[PDB]
Image 1 (cartoon, rainbow, N blue to C red):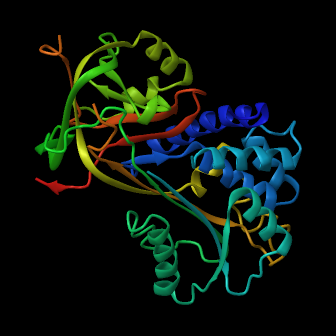
Image 2 (image 1 turned 135 degrees about the horizontal axis):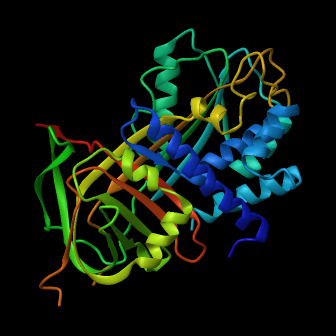
Image 3 (image 1 turned 180 degrees about the vertical axis):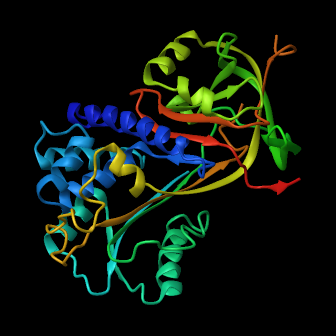
Length: 366
């Protein structure tokens, strides 16, 4: 159980995660989305720790923590981060140019609250800068996320890299042999070859006949958290369903869910997703930190015009059969052969661990 300050922070982190998801969803260039509320919030936390003036005040403002002491914010976020590690691999590293020396004070507090790593890189050798970043992320995730980016767009600033590996462990496992090859319809005209895992059990279920979708809750190990899937009836873009995706609607839907026999089929595999949150952070209210001529990160370094060039949110999410061990002849069918939205929620608190969408699984494009 979290402190009231850490609990209030957690609420805002999900509010932020939804706002971020929506922003990205609007980008036609975006396919799969994968966001960890807390990791996003700790990126803003780092800006507040590293910044001065509106640069830092905006970070607290996006986090709706303006009525909290700076240390109360860092403590709370650091609490929430620690609460995640008790299947889960997380690394945080700040990359600055070779010419930039990080402030001892900043290094101390960032390591203390955010478990932030610091490294100097040289983008005069792009192959080596990239190799460093990718190698670091690969070790952090033990190879699950081998590459974070193929290119570093902006080289005049600081690079925040968050490498993650998450693997939901079912409270009732899928049988290791209940796996076969199936087509996943990315669009009505494009099918990719995937491996599907199949299982029938009692699950919290809701079929919204009015808004043409299905909602299922798959509890994770020891019912401490659960995975919720929202899938439209038809093979269609997630645009329509995303318009309904609000905190309030989600609450309405969950109230309507009841424990029924459900035949769940999911694409089995690792989904590697890398986001550069920098573009969407300006949209959330973090306008100064991300501009060379606006940014003030003087508490972080003192180097002329250092600004936050990138915020890499790279995640390897694995859908596997593994989970805990141990009427049903006519179950409701929940066959995920087209794009769906998913959430990971902490059972006890209601806090959002993850928000994302699966649009293109890793597989053989037919």
